[PDB]
Length: 290
Length: 296
DNA sequence: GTGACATCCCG
DNA sequence: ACATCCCG
Ligand SMILES: [Mg+2]
Ligand SMILES: [Mg+2]
Image (cartoon, rainbow over all chains, first blue to last red):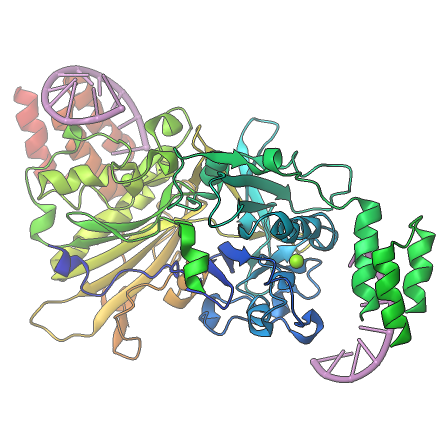
């Protein structure tokens, strides 16, 4: 019965997973963006001598150029290029970091968001490695509806470039953290949904928190399926802080990262009512005397 | 490496092929609709004892109810439950028809478009069976962008129901036909995208025709991968008519049908009043079903 | 909640 | 566009 139906094959969705040195993903050929991107983080992965300024954005060679995004779509569009698996999670491997610049990892993102609030969540994930031995993170874009005047719910999103790359309304991140491979403690988990726009330091990460069941219904995905849900799972914002770097800390940490790449860093640093920490002063003198 | 990544598995998109008796589809768990639906038509298949009335729409059992559409999402939505694998194409099997009524084969479709223009395409699909041995149809939904005045391109589609089933702006349909298992005539292929609006009889099917490559880029799909593009493939609107039923033929057909259904003299007496009020010439075939029903 | 089975309407 | 420079 089916040999006749399947004579000329079935339409190909391009849905199959694609693993890389340190991240996997499913690609949406219609939207020219990922559907989901999964990564693993540890204290050792965020340490290394891999440099982001050395990488470059470019289409995933493993993606058929037909349904591939291109830098020509992003540049000048008013939207930035936001990796769903940060380069900063692949300090250990310059290769893994390079694969996170394949445009199959990137979506159109608000500049202030990509560098601001969203960035600070990526930071909060790498922080979880100081308290957890293993941290799994799934990220992806979303195009959610908006009820308006007539009460009709309308999904409305922009598409940029000659290839009409979908610009998402919100971004999501599902953080799964395990204390250790030998601990009896339950797993920490929390879903979050951020709007693709500038967000200040006033809103807390907990405000953008959603339930996993809801994020699955909206994204149409089932996250971490092997994970037993009747088993004991805990809220990551209850076990942990769900605390992002406030303006002071956040501005302090950036300066810590800039000195490695001089006299202007300190000048703008103090102007913003910041007291250079000893951890920053130490790194300052070392780089100052080099 | 992967061992560490996959430790709890990857997220499930639910896009794996789902084969049924006489059709296959890839479901969209987010949009609550199929991405593509692949059916096969033949002379024998459009002929059988299968009757629509016996069937009803219902959520597809194979789909997780979390990502399933429901009749409650459609009823009162202002939209109809339009099937992508038609029931009229599965009249030979009592089960293959019933499976088309799974909401995984359905999209929210304009009432007029579904029983009007879209219908004539599905009729013309079943009409290709006369001129062709085998026919392969791949129909599905679309949410195409629209350019504003300032230059932004925007995808703006509607969502309905508690479960938020997406309402496509357009529907597409790829036709692929073979003359006979015996013959050798190169295959006939055509691709068409139809707005989800009410369409008159004024437009003809060649107007809504787009390239397969174009349809593939817009949909994000590659249709019939095995089919060699280098091979001799024929524009089905050159080897065949690509002719739908005009108003007269179409109005004649429905009138012919509504007779047996009608259960009074007024209705039957009005059916013909519509043809002569619409300037249609009743044919002898209809004069029989009319005069026979008149006796009764 | 849906299988079957009646009833009715429209394009 | 491509090299050199600057944003959050
Ligand atoms: Mg980024
Ligand atoms: Mg229909």
